[PDB]
Amino acid sequence: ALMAKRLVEELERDGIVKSERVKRALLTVPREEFVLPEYRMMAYEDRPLPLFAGATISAPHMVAMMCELIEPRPGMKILEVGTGSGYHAAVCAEAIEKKGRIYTIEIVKELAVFAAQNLERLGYWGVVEVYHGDGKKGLEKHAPFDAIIVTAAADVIPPALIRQLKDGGVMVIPVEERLGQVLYKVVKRGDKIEKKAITYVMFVPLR
Ligand SMILES: Nc1ncnc2c1ncn2[C@@H]1O[C@H](CSCC[C@H](N)C(=O)O)[C@@H](O)[C@H]1O
C-alpha cells in the first residue's frame, strides 16, 4: 500500500499521471499479482521486471503514459496488443471503472495462459478477455475499438489497426525509428489520420 502510494505520487510530480482517474487505477492495481513470485519484492519499483518468453511487465511509467494518452472514460471497448502479464489490461479495466471491455491479444500461448490466470485471481475476467494470436492482425471479431494500446514496438504502423480504430479512437503505438523507439499517439478523424509523437520509449519489439 505505502510503496503504491509513493509510486503514483512520484509519477504525478514527474508529470506522467496527469489524470486522477489513471492514478486511481494504478493505486488499485496490484502489480505484485502480475509479476512472478520472486519479483514481488521489486514489483512497486518503476522499472520493467523480467517475465518468461521475452515478455517484460511494462514499467508503471510506461503504463500511465499509455492510459493517459487513450483518454480513459467509462464504457470503452479497448484492444491491448501484447498482453504479456496482463498488468496493463487490469489498469485499463479500473480506468474505465469495469464498464466496457478490454480485449487483449498475445502471440505466446504460454503467456496468454498466465495473463488470463492473473486476471481471474483479482476479478477482471469478463471485463478483460485474452486471445492467443497476432497483434498485427488484431481482433476483427470485436472491432471497431475506442482505444488500441500496442504494448510492443512496431517497425511500421500496422494498417489493420488504423482500420480497426473507430472514429475518434486513440492508438498508442511505439514505433522503432532512428535513435530508438518513439511513443506515438494516432487519432482518427473519420477518414483522416493524426499521427502525433510523444517521448522516446524503450519497448520489446512486435512479432
Ligand atoms: N505480434 C505480436 N502479437 C501479439 N503479442 C505480441 C506480439 N509480439 C510480441 N507480443 C507479446 O507482447 C508482450 C510484450 S510485454 C507487454 C506487457 C504489458 N504491458 C503488461 O504489463 O501486461 C510479450 O508477452 C510478447 O510475447
Image (cartoon, rainbow, N blue to C red):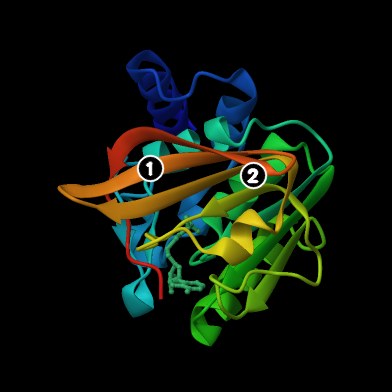
Which residue does the numbered mark 1 point to in the structure image? 183
Q: Is the residue under label 2 in contact with that under label 1 (CB below 8 Å)?
A: no
Residue 199 to residue 33: above or below: above
Horizontal placement of 173 versus 140: left or right? left
Measured as percent of width and height from the top left, residue 19 is found at 57, 20
Measured as percent of width and height from the top left, residue 15 is found at 39, 18
Horizontal placement of 110 versus 113: left or right? left
The answer to which quarter of the image holds residue 69 is top right
Horizontal placement of 133 versus 63: left or right? right
Residue occupying the point 39% across, 50% down? 174
**What residue type is disc 2 on?**
Cys
- Classify 10 Å Cα crowding around label 2: few (below 14), some (14-19), many (20 and above): many
Which residue does the numbered mark 2 point to in the structure image? 92
Q: In the image shown, does 130 or 123 lie closer to the viewer?
A: 130
Residue at disc 2, secondary structure: helix
Q: Quadrant of the C terminus?
A: bottom left
Q: In the image shown, does 123 or 54 lie closer to the viewer?
A: 54
**What residue type is disc 1 on?**
Leu
